[PDB]
Image 1: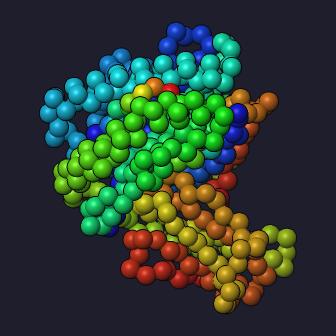
Image 2: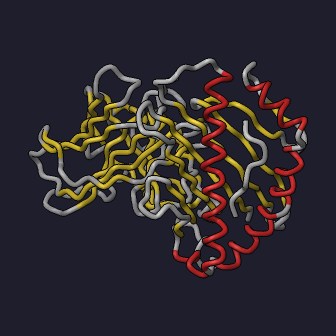
Length: 99
Length: 276
Length: 9
């Protein structure tokens, strides 16, 4: 039976506007292992997202780190959208640089 | 300190394509060092950290034949489980396994592990005694009787007490100036105004390995579990981890609040406040 | 070193 994914979106490094960085979308605690992850800039899919290999925790649940290069600005908004069988609709979370 | 080795194996069936995908990941001290994947063009145990390239072709060829054996083992087991649970065709199914050993700091076996899950759910496990089996499910009882009658537990006990220990000893010596490191966290506190008369203080810990860590807040004395928000520890993507914990606080009376960071790389717990 | 399994389930 299904386990719904938990998502966090955050930068690898302290975010500074105009300085290149890496944006992460860490998706954990899900089952079954088949999942769809897109990272978004201003609502549009970012085309070249790196996907770590499938792994699982000692509680049997799966997790994945997705990441991409990006340059934070004052104006653009980033997000991660996750499609999985535990959810009737996709789940979006937005990047907040303070959290 | 203490040490461990684990192999985490997975086989996934899907309605269409004619054979399950099988994947095995090995870890030494919770860090990846080998990997086999049946979807790969060259299905073979490839190395995963610099220090494993010391192994000759005879090591990789044996390990790879082992993985091919496991794949077929997972394949038949998946079939058998479908029947045991009166599941029809046309669905997706998961079989997972964890196995390995924990050594103490004295390099002796502390514990062996062998565990299986079906559909993400405990199916059967070898008990700590390495002699008897735990299986909760009615369906799992068939596997348990089969394995009791075949002396399966003896076979796994020998691997866990023998090969698992002997070869982990070997792996630690090869990467000694590699896995004998821990990065201490760097903590700082940030300040975030909210609904006035109040403000969120957010304690950050960055660049640490391994992932286990604890962040507390104190109102001048006693810890605060309510309503202290935190996030789950997360990979930064470069081998290190990040965490924060926050507490909401009266504006102006915020120098009363202290944050502590507990990590195994610290010579002692760190202590921190908001610094305007 | 990987385990190799005994009887199937």
